[PDB]
Amino acid sequence: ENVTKDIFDLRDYYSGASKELKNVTGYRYSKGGKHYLIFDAHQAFTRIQIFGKDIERLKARKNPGLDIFVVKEAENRTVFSYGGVTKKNQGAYYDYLNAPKFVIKKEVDAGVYTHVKRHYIYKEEVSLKELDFKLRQYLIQNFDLYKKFPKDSKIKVIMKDGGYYTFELNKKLQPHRMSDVIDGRNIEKMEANIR
Ligand SMILES: CC(=O)N[C@@H]1[C@@H](O[C@@H]2O[C@@H](C)[C@@H](O)[C@@H](O)[C@@H]2O)[C@H](O[C@@H]2O[C@H](CO)[C@H](O)[C@H](O[C@]3(C(=O)O)C[C@H](O)[C@@H](NC(C)=O)[C@H]([C@H](O)[C@H](O)CO)O3)[C@H]2O)[C@@H](CO)O[C@H]1O
Ligand SMILES: [Cl-]
Image 1 (tube, protein in one colour):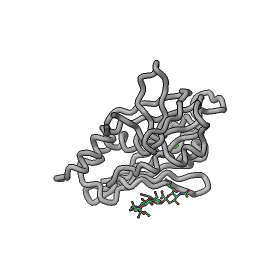
Image 2 (cartoon, rainbow, N blue to C red):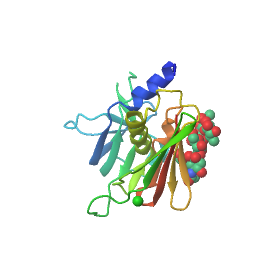
Image 3 (spheres, helix red, strand yellow):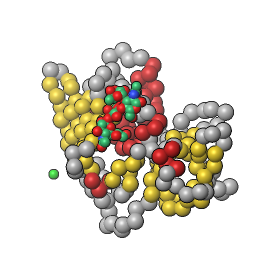
Image 4 (cartoon, rainbow, N blue to C red):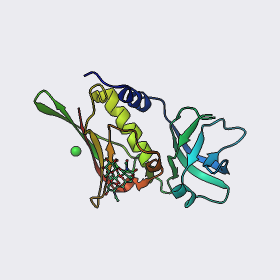
């Protein structure tokens, strides 16, 4: 299929680099009525822009023990990443916390091809920013996501109580959702329906 540049950009975004910061200390900083987390003379890390809902869980200024999922976003002024902040595990685990199956269904030649796989969850608090990125990346590399027009392609994260989270794959995840945090242990199963 003969896809437009916004699909290319989505493909480039989601197979770009990402970086997991763990148990890091971040410092609160506002400049021009926007809210950021910064680090240390010594940690030449990407600036994290944060949101209203992040503030409600952060402290006046210094903030140890954070886990950040960083994705470089492209230039303003300087380079930023949106959201992806969570608290470190409190529990101690042998390996992972949860392994819900990720059932991948791909429309094809008058058929559907299904692949089941496990997705290994390490964090008590996992942001939607991270499940969106890693999942779509996986699907780009292993299932040809964004080679054809995605149309209604969706990822669904389904919880134990039945509550779910949907990632419409024809658009980038809206900024304000990158700070939504769900409980890693209560993820029941995961679904993708794609072309
Ligand atoms: C113009 C625009 O983009 N508006 C945004 C909303 O999206 C629009 O409305 C939805 C219903 C769809 O029609 C979109 O195509 C349309 O653009 C946006 O609403 C949210 O959209 C997402 C998908 O983009 C999804 O449908 C959200 O609903 C759920 C979900 O399926 O993920 C419904 C779940 O019950 C709820 N889960 C709970 C409560 O456990 C979740 C959950 O709150 C979120 O997943 C947390 O991120 O949402 C639907 O809300 C809206 C909200 O982000 O923003 C508008 O800008
Ligand atoms: Cl099994």
